[PDB]
Image: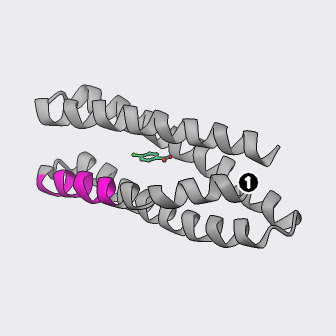
Amino acid sequence: SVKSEYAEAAAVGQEAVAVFNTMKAAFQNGDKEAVAQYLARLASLYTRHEELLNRILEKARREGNKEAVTLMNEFTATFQTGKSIFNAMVAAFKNGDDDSFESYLQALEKVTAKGETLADQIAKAL
Ligand SMILES: O=C(O)c1ccc(Cl)cc1
């Protein structure tokens, strides 16, 4: 159901957290080769999560689930903010700008955490 599809989306989000934290570690340690591979992994995760999120949103819409639609619209907007910062980070990595990479790493953390207390409102609304 929409709810099993949400637990699958939540698990991909958790896969991103795990990989992001091992990417941050590699960045701090200077292992650019690893960072490069982690950024590719995280790109695919974002893409996969965004597709699971769109299917959940469209499903909630077809189901007339107004509250779920409101919360999903708010969550995906925030999700997109994190994606846009991620893309800026990838660009900082290609350009050799470590000052910006570190900054984006931090802002992407704060934007992802903020979107968490809502993630547990969607779950109960679907
Ligand atoms: O899909 C997510 O939740 C997600 C994906 C990628 C990053 Cl870097 C951070 C969060």
The quarter in which the C terminus is drawn is bottom right
Taking the spot 71% from the left edge, 65% from the top edge, the residue there is 68
To which quarter of the image does residue 48 belong? top right
Query: Taking the image as drawn, is residue 87 in sight?
Result: no
Residue 79 in the figure: left or right of residue 58: left
| Amino acid on which disc 1 is placed | Ile
Taking the spot 56% from the left edge, 35% from the top edge, the residue there is 11
Magenta stretch encompasses residue 35: no
Q: How is the image coloured?
A: one colour
The quarter in which the N terminus is drawn is top right
Neighbourhood count class around disc 1 (C-alpha, 10 Å): few under 14, some 14–19, many 20 upward = many
Taking the spot 41% from the left edge, 59% from the top edge, the residue there is 82
Residue 15 in the figure: left or right of residue 6: left
Q: Position of residue 25 (x, y in %)?
A: 20, 32
Q: Main SS of the magenta segment?
A: helix
Q: Position of residue 88 (x, y in %)?
A: 33, 59
User: 8 above or below 114?
Assistant: above
User: 98 above or below 121?
Assistant: above
As drawn, which residue projects farthest toward the front?
124
Q: Which residues are magenta?
A: 99-110
Taking the spot 68% from the left edge, 47% from the top edge, the residue there is 52
Residue 119 in the figure: left or right of residue 6: left
- Between 31 and 28, the one lying in front of the other is 28
To which quarter of the image does residue 42 belong? top left
User: 123 above or below 118?
Assistant: above
Query: Which residue in the structure is indicated by mark 1?
Result: 56
Q: Position of residue 115 (x, y in %)?
A: 45, 60
Query: Taking the image as drawn, is residue 91 in sight?
Result: yes
